[PDB]
Image (tube, coloured by chain):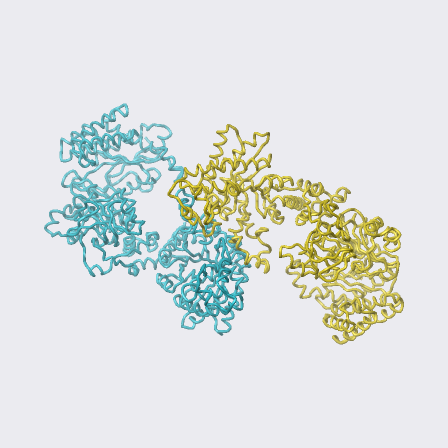
Chain colours: A yellow, B cyan
Amino acid sequence: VAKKWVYYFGGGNADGNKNMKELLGGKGANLAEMVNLGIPVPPGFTITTEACKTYQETETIPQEVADQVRENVSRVEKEMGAKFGDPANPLLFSVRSGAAASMDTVLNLGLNKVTVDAWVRRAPRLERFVYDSYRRFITMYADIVMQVGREDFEEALSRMKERRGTKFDTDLTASDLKELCDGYLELFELKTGCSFPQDPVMQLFAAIKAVFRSWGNPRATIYRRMNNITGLLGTAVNVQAMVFGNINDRSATGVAFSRSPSTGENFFFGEYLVNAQGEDVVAGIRTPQQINHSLSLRWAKAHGVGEEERRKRYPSMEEAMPENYRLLCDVRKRLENHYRDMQDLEFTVQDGRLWLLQCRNGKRTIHAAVRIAIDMVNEGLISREEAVLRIDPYQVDHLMHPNLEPGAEKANKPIGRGLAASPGAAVGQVVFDAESAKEWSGRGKKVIMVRLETSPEDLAGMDAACGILTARGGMTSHAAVVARGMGKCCVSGCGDMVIRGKSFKLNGSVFREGDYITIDGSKGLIYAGKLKLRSPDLKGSFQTILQWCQEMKRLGVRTNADTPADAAKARSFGAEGVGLCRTEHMFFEGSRINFIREMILADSASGRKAALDKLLPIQRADFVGILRAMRGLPVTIRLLDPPLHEFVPHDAAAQFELAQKLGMPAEKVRNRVNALHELNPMLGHRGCRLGITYPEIYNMQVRAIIEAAIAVSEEGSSVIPEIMVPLVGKKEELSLIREEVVKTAEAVITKSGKRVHYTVGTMIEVPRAAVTADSIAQKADFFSFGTNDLTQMGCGFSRDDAGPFLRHYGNLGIYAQDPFQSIDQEGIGELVRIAVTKGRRVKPMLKMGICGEHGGDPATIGFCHKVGLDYVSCSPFRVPVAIVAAAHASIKDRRAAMK
Amino acid sequence: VAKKWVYYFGGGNADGNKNMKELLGGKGANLAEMVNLGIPVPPGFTITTEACKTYQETETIPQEVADQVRENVSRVEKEMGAKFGDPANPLLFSVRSGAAASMDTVLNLGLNKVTVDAWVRRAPRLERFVYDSYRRFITMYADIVMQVGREDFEEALSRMKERRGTKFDTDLTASDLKELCDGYLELFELKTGCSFPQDPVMQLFAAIKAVFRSWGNPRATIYRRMNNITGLLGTAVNVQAMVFGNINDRSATGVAFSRSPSTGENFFFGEYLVNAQGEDVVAGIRTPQQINHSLSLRWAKAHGVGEEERRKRYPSMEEAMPENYRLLCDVRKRLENHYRDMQDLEFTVQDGRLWLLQCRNGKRTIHAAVRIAIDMVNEGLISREEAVLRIDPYQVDHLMHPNLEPGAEKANKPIGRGLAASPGAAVGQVVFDAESAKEWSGRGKKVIMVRLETSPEDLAGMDAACGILTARGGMTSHAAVVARGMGKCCVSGCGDMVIRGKSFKLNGSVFREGDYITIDGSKGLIYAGKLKLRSPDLKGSFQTILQWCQEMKRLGVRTNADTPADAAKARSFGAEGVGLCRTEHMFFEGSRINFIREMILADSASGRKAALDKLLPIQRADFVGILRAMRGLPVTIRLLDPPLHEFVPHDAAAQFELAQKLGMPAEKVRNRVNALHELNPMLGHRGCRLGITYPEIYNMQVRAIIEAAIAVSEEGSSVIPEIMVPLVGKKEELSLIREEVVKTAEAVITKSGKRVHYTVGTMIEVPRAAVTADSIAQKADFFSFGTNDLTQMGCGFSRDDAGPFLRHYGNLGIYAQDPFQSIDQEGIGELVRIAVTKGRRVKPMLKMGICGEHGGDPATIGFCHKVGLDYVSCSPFRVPVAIVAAAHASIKDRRAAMK
């Protein structure tokens, strides 16, 4: 001999190991890893990628690959005890493809007539099941391994469902299925020339050859284009013994989570069923049993159940099968210790003997991920660094979900109980199918969805509805799973609920599209619809994660905020200053609007100057109001941005009459109004443009600042203002405005006899500024990137007008995503790239930042990190997300540069 | 000895030569060059830059620089005959600075009391003149060489003008001036401590030291910053003997042009005066005499003069001073042969002896430059290449000036005659001072300006007025000169005109702000105001220059034109195709507007499709109309650009009623009208955006083309259309539209069974396209640069709105010039630079062009050449200018790469 084409696994030893993902594919390496690890995985063997390649380039399987496969089957037989192809003690295989990177899966390989009507006449509780599986398998076979369609078995099935009068397979009987199978057998012996392979070994090779075929598959040769991992070899094949927990009453299957995927709490959560095929566990019919004792005790304590009932009706793996729960408990510890993470587990006790069928890093809610992470830090399982990475910024918003307040005893009203399937609380009128809820969302109405059980076709309406409430289902209930997949508060398995039409009766009371509420506490109610923001968020829980994020973050996180109310909110998530405080608002709402309306009119520059010293203190006051919020912290303020025509009506009478002297009615109104009107206001007279034709403004503004600025300084604190000039396009556009502010500022400083440190700098929002960024650097003290504006000019999109088509672009996939939400990295970013480099060539230590909506978007933030920006600025309620996303980018980099 | 600090010139030999511009400055090198050349320049010497430097770094003049200056004065004395400082035969100097690169000039150095009241008592015809010069000189001295102001001599002068009752120096007499001088003498001996230097030699050194001082001058240290020729040494000094043509009646001064600065014709044009100081020649009082015989004969033949009159009253240098005209004729030939160009000459016959005081490449009108250039090619003086370079593209517009038609005998009416001072003809109401004309321009009124004589304070109104007509002045008349400086048609020296108030009487008839006309034929009229475009321009004259330009040009010159009327006009200046034919117009004016109005409404896509096949042939027809113009030539067509909201009213009733069926009044008008309204229409739904939401349009358009396109092909010709897609921003924005046209095109081709070669390509007008130009290349066949649009987005300027401030920017000098007229090379250009390189990286042989207004602007064109574009496209009436400007850039480059 020489070559080795096949790799056994199971004996606790396993030929291969966790390193050969090249030969055994990831599934196969993983399996190997697992058994060497010592966990009880049903046996089988792996067929190396080389084997696969040898098949593509010639439609053959080498004789020594055959021999070799036979060599191992006889090993699997030995290990399990059964015998492949022997109707007395049969052994069945599952055949699956090796490579997580995406070709399908076959159960019950090894089924044939003899083995069937000898298994039935041998344990006839399961006569229904056997035929179910045979017809299932016969179909799987012809479809996949023979490529002969299904539209035919599908038809002859339903043709048999109408003959008995249901719509469900669930009602077909042993006798029906047998009929089904028997027709399938000849329907097969027709659609193709031959009869269904009774020889389980031919069946086997057929399987193998069909997996190797599923690789060159056209539906798959594409795969390697736009997944682009070229040069792979082929795919492994994983043959594996089948096991069952519906054999007898010392058999079970179940599903379990090393830690709660909702609370996150450290207990052994699970569900099982004696003599049951998992399916039944999910199904929800027939109440699922808790694996752990404590946990049963409390499910019971939170329903009408007393001990002597649960004891004999709904036990607990811990006491029903204690031997094994003890061991399943070991395995739980074992794998958590290995993978360093919450696992979820599928298992099966076939005849007293425990098997672990499937094991994955477990999905979880955001709350849960936050907990487990902290715990495993403490427990010593992972680093704080590692912790942080297991928290998704996209999900950090889910912590901003409302739950109830003690207004749950303000009045009671729990007219029902279920599972605490998904954290949260939700109000809403109800609706009874995917399409019901698909609709009321759109009328402005928030909706609770109620279905007996949900499914992947109740799905569209699922992420529409504000809440979900099902009649049946465990913690593994479909609704349950998917709800946590979106952190959409859910209560499931409430079997008291009787559903009929668009109504349902919750013990006592009856309901229809009225207003309900549900909770993660798991109780159905009828409003108490005073939710609350969990704004004192996660009680130093999340806050700890943020601390850590603060420690590995490189980028500073500042806030976009112009109310001190908005300043201090954002600061108290640990924002470190403002990257954008816009001064328009202290010209608009309230008393202010009028006196600007006076200035723009004043047919005289010495005139307006008076219309100005009017507004000195109304603003100056709004500025202490802001500077007071950020004591010790930097604040960037964008001087008046827009055109004067937004401060004026069209017709109003009330304005011209506050008035000055005569020679003046309501068409020196219409003069400068249709006089100040523009075609494309966006690119009209504003920003610096405006502040150079009429300068004294930027001066009032500038003292309004430095007046307020020096004031606060006195009061035992320190303050640094960053004067920003909008819309600058050319080096000299800015150079003038500069001494135009350094005038006002240096005057207030001289007159006041007391010093304060300001800096003048510009928005980079015009494309030209980007390109000429080097020269613009000489007059500047920092850059804020106005990527919003800069995207509109960069792309030629007047945001408010791109409705008709942008949405459309998203579909056919021009821009992967609204570039006003996440930066166009290919283009708009290049502009930024260009700016950052040229600018730093000149001033190498130039402060650079970004602001607006992109400021809070992770992907963008990550880009900003790479590109070299100094800080990011975002709205208050993103501060958290950003802080994470930042530390998140910094973390990835620190590791990359370590290899 | 060793060093040589001073360089004599004059003896026909001249120490230095034309190469030492480093020591002798350009004036000094030039002088040297001149005399070695053999032309009679009044003698003098040059004081090397080294001398200058030695003075800055110590306020001294080396003893050997003194000695040396004395050495040469005694050489000048020898040469001329006079004696410096000897009141019997005095010699006077002019002292001027050496370096054309910009410090001033002093005449009559060497004047002192003795020399004066001995010159007077020695030839007292000139007693007036001597004192004039002395007071002049005394002032020049104190101002410049003593830096003591003038506000004082100026005052004491005018204080003496009021005492005699005029406003003019012209009236002050010998006796007055003597008084003036005598007070100046003590006014000097006061303003400073000492009396006026009688010692002409001290006077000399003083001169020298003051020139060296005028170099370190603050008003001059600036000079070297923003002229930036750092490291110069200093400045030379040019001392030179003074000469006079007012000595006797065998003395003259004059001014002459080796070829006519108006017609360009090859004759000796000039003007002189016997016993006259040039000044008198310009002045216009006392009729100027022609230098050449022929030329006198014809001036006379074109006024009331007979031979026996001119013979004794207004002779001719040719026959008055024949000896010398013969020689001045030689010199003319000599210098033209040397400088290879039309010269103009200032001269002076002092006592029978000819001197040439000044000689420069002569300014000329565009017509003239075109002639002389051609002639000197033929004559063998210069190459065709060189020719081309002596033609300014900025002036090529001046050939587009109107002159009369034979409608000058349609009716006569020449109620006057003057000089043909400046080519052209002009209609207009008249006005009588700079401010008169400064005004009527602005009322839409075109104005003729009439002044006895003009001057540098009649100047603002000068370039306002459509024409100029003066009462006095030769070909050297101020008005004359400056008129040719702008090619503004002018008639001067019409002494028949008597001016009074805002009236004047032209022999017979009297006039006031009525409507006149003037001509380069030199006759005043009263309309015949049917001018004509000299559109059959320059009779193969200019056309020859264009041929040549065509032969050295690199860039192709295409035209921006969408009427076949506009196509063939531009082609017949030799434009080589269209770079922009915009298809909006065949949706608007006339029948078409209605049926588009139908499409935009058709609430149904299959609906509009019918509203389309409507417009197939109205356009298809407009396309043969265009394709017929450019047979053999390329035509680029920009598919529909704009938004639908420009094809709709606001209120109209007439539209909804052409109508379809019921359920439809005048607020399914207002729906889609305020529904299709945008905030910034510029960046709204259009170009490709529009052609992807509604595609069938770009299809109608595309067949409308290729239908018309194949048609023309049949008719014995060949045609190539270049389908251009507006507004493309992303690689895939275009990629779709592409097969979206290749569909329609490949269909029409298949259905027609006959082939035609199209190309699809895009406008580069969005900044993002520029930056991502590499990827956009893969789907394109050419680039047209939409630098208009691209400047608006690039700069953030909505052109129609930039009124309020752009004009202002121009003043303080942000942008040197409206960037919508000439490309912002620093920024918008960089974008282009970026585009061109990235694009060519991908497709190296990509066709690239530019269009719009920048297309015709030289400076921009020159940029386009450097940057590597393939063609330029401009409006018909720029084609010429562009062709020149192109060949002009290509020419410069060919020479640069040869060294």
Image coordinates for residue B571, horizontal then vertical, percent: 37, 62
Q: Quadrant of the N terminus of chain A?
A: bottom right
Residue that protrudes farthest toward the left in the picture: B308
Residue A841 appears in the figure: no
Q: Quadrant of residue B277?
A: top left
Toward the viewer: A876 or B232? A876
Q: Is residue A398 above or below residue B44?
A: below
Toward the viewer: A118 or A67? A118
Q: Quadrant of residue A346?
A: bottom right
Q: Quadrant of residue A499?
A: bottom right
Image coordinates for residue A752, horizontal then vertical, percent: 50, 29
Report the side of B596 relative to B488 (left or right): right
Q: Is residue B747 above or below residue B71?
A: below
Image coordinates for residue A690, horizontal then vertical, percent: 45, 43
Report the side of A813 relative to B21 (left or right): right
> Could you tell me how many numbered marks the image carries?
0
Residue B18 appears in the figure: yes
Residue that protrudes farthest toward the top in the picture: B193
Image coordinates for residue B34, horizontal then vertical, percent: 27, 43
Toward the viewer: B382 or B256? B256
